Image 1: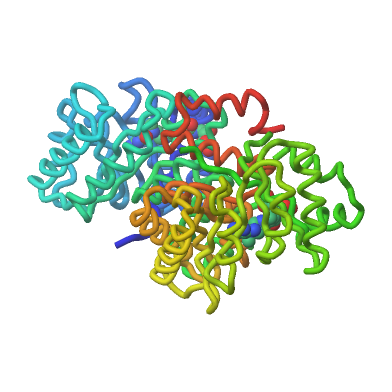
Image 2: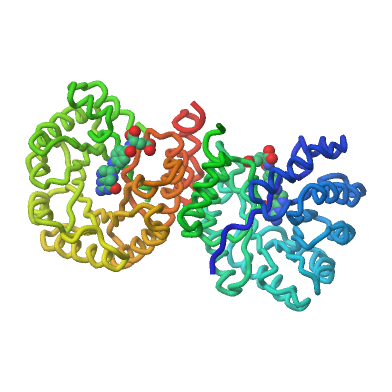
Length: 271
Length: 267
Ligand SMILES: CN1c2c(nc(N)[nH]c2=O)NC[C@@H]1CNc1ccc(C(=O)N[C@@H](CCC(=O)O)C(=O)O)cc1
Ligand SMILES: CN1c2c(nc(N)[nH]c2=O)NC[C@@H]1CNc1ccc(C(=O)N[C@@H](CCC(=O)O)C(=O)O)cc1
């Protein structure tokens, strides 16, 4: 039961020097422009990540959430490695979006799951635990099962969950995409209504022409069954690959979306 | 295994090549042969002239190509008699492009190659034309392999081309390509499956973008060889990145070496 890839726009992230500077400077215009441009490029969710010191995170996420929601109604994806921070900002969202993320580490599921029980929030769940990020397929598939079982005990349906198998660098494991595809097959076999999600950038660390590698990884992971991804939709070459691959996978009737993005100059040479 | 690359550029349909043929421009043909350095395993040669000029044209292109490179020839003609008349001009065995169940293509070509090391591209079509489903193509592939085995031609010498059709004509074109490839290689694990890239993107804009993403998807689906333009640097980067992503480039070295030599990446 296939569907277009769900795009989580990654650009409002304080690890990016220009955004860290905008947060320090309180430059709303930059954040507003990234929210709007990503929405216009087709993002389904706008990721927001403070990447500041811990005791500034909550107030910075609230500031980012305010600016994004003034500019656009595209729902938020709240990105924090600190579940307490997510808890403290969830009420600032005007509508339900995505929480990024829970995992089996520490008390992430004990904090976040009661937080979204009975709501329409969706959640990204990473296949990692207190021992770290496993490289092998079996361990990640077992973590996903445990996460889905813990979510079920708060009445969170599989359709609300996006499992992120945390693909590692191809230079660290040349089987990284093969394992990604095999974990995706096994997870979806167990849970046919679940989503599988990934970032695009980790795969190319340690290789030249990262943008080339990331774009080929996207195409392969889409064919392997990826449902959502955290990516940069302002990258015109990546967007042309995404839309060509949607048409090649039979998901763009009469190739109309591809033809329209070309006609509007969203992809191809900048006119 | 790494994808087998049949370099497509020496084809008289391309106006610069047509003109070089008419001028006897040797340098232009040698240069395409030698540059297709880019990794080609076979150099396609296709005259694309009138019927009565094709044999002498092919002999000229084969002569000039083999002066430039020892990379073997892929002799591309729709006329099996032309292939018969030029096979002896090759200095070493290569690929014949192509046979199919149409007319007498198998009956002319297979006796010439029986007991030799020549390989052959075999298209899934017959006298009624290009087939109208996946099943028909898989059944034609089975008939081609059986005809070939009656001349002692092993499956590893055959590259079955399932003749992918334009995505704008049928939005399932790649889904069906991948299904036929999976079924053919299930029946015959030692056979190769091959394709051209360009047909898929007919009637769409940004055809090079569509061709490149079709390459990456078809490689994951199991394609073994492809006739393509390996002088297109963006296509070669995608081809090499996809080889590394499919676990076929140990420590991503071929990719890193191609970047370090400026074979891919900004000029
Ligand atoms: C680890 N990634 C990740 C995640 N969240 C989850 N669940 N999974 C993930 O893999 N959150 C953080 C990051 C995804 N976000 C980002 C954000 C920006 C860039 C980045 O490098 N941006 C550059 C280059 C963009 C491009 O290549 O087009 C930029 O200049 O904005 C990478 C990842
Ligand atoms: C039908 N294609 C084909 C085949 N043989 C078989 N077995 N299968 C096939 O699909 N032989 C002919 C052709 C492949 N040959 C070619 C040769 C050149 C171009 C061509 O359009 N070349 C342009 C564009 C190059 C590019 O996109 O990089 C050129 O300028 O060279 C297309 C197909």
